[PDB]
Length: 256
Length: 257
Ligand SMILES: N[C@@H](CCC(=O)O)C(=O)O
Ligand SMILES: N[C@@H](CCC(=O)O)C(=O)O
Image (cartoon, rainbow over all chains, first blue to last red; front, side, top):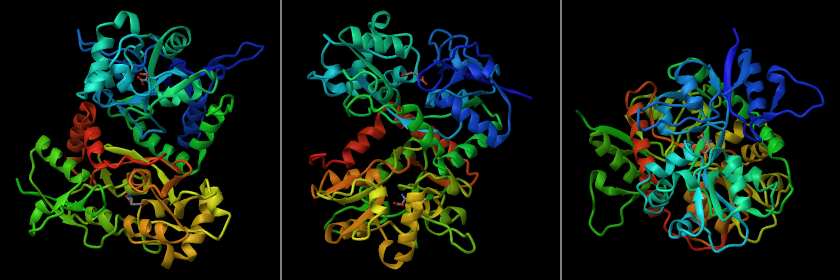
């Protein structure tokens, strides 16, 4: 039996492979998470079918009714066996789904343009001329919501009282807003690293604000979770996780 | 309920002896990021505890021949302690014999040497012989190099293993003192490197993180505290408390970097 693997389109983790002819099935995707998924299947010996989350969402809990959406809800309802995606392992998701050990470490940081007085979230928090936000219903947005730290709680009051105007639906939308307006985008440092190598005008501002991991998600209590953690340890041991990251982030396009 | 026995090891700034004129007793002897963490866990979960330094002074690694563990790891396996609240690296070989909470801090292995050196990576360090290098004996960093199949790290282990008696040292403080007085580069965890370099401007990290892992609270295999501790650390992490404690103990922030 074939495991259903739910994912989401996000460069350079998961993308449509470019070719002159129609591609079908798993063959039509490529990226870091497609390579990882492939290495996992050959270690653990399963077959799989990749499907993109119908929602287009990562997975947040809505306050009004306590229900999840996105990739998390797909695993909650057992419509997927695994989620191989840049899905952040967070405490609020660990209550409803299970994660393998992280296959990559990252943090929330700020994507903005080179050449400004802003050099930390602290500088953003204390003003309102430069708008900022994050992907709505992602892990970054939940960081700000739960923090009892002045700077981050103040950034959440700002974003919160301007939801319909400063929260974006995807990273690409946030990236487009940084490039076309006075807007700073809170997003994950791994993605920022990929993005600032293709746009020399963009830069990560300040350091990492938190620290987290991407792990493969599974429904709560499933037995593949421990198998997958052991496969990830082996790939880490062998340097393959590292090789996969140089391959997908290879692009000495801009100066660092 | 009885007090939990917590095993730990002296290591600035995680765990140290409070500075005082008069002598202190029990738990009152210690201070540090870890001791603060322990204190917070105890009130979140409601337990009393007694802190005991690991008898053999090691974090824990496996014997070459029989594969028996030593250090804090071995104390947990043997049930001599209920928890290990220390900068204990969560690693795959350790997870086979003890349980860890979710990590309260992430880090990686890096290199500590003097500023001014042309060495800029472990690959650089492996190809020369004027500069010696090593790690804390019987900890997660030594184990990393010992098990590595990556060419550069395997080359380094061949060196540290042959000069073992001299280059593997008993603690971070001993390795740091070797960096400051001899041509010796020290393989160690980035959090600790960050503590040191912020306070001594003659010292620097060389290269990036050599690998990546977290610190976690160790518990004996299958203990019920594991999930309760994970739950507490999540509370502390979400709200911003771990960050506030990191800032309190990594105080020194004063060098070009
Ligand atoms: N990777 C995030 C989505 C994007 C973000 O929140 O920055 C998640 O797992 O929710
Ligand atoms: N923190 C390490 C010890 C120090 C090191 O290996 O550099 C451990 O848990 O073993």
